[PDB]
Length: 89
Length: 58
Image 1: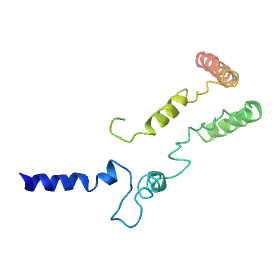
Image 2: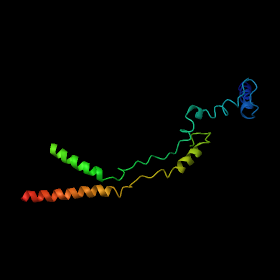
Image 3: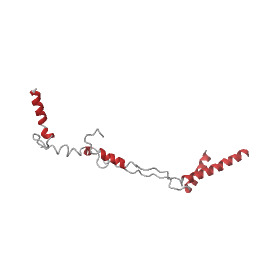
Image 4: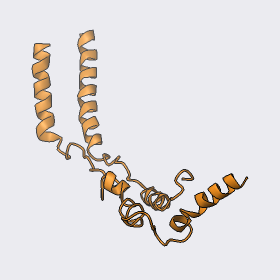
């Protein structure tokens, strides 16, 4: 069907200079290559956070420590305050 | 990864995860201080345990 044929040939070929050969675009007055693959290519890193979330920050955890190796001057206080609790107990 | 047809980053952040695959280790650092706390605890415990065993029979 040459209706279908000529329709599909113009359908294929009229944007084929926008897809097959990159002679960017004749009817569109703004250029097409600085829309999606140049501006909007960094789109998702213009739409999400840059240099922390997309670079993802493989980050070292803060090494949380013990009671800093001091028994004496606080274990005696814990012992005497425990005497005071057992007074109150 | 086969979802994104225009991939270009999934091997990058894949390698970024496999870089940080030795993530970070923990700490069972306490082998000097925790023995001191259980030493004081076991000392007071054995003192109290023998004391009340004496005082019950007394």
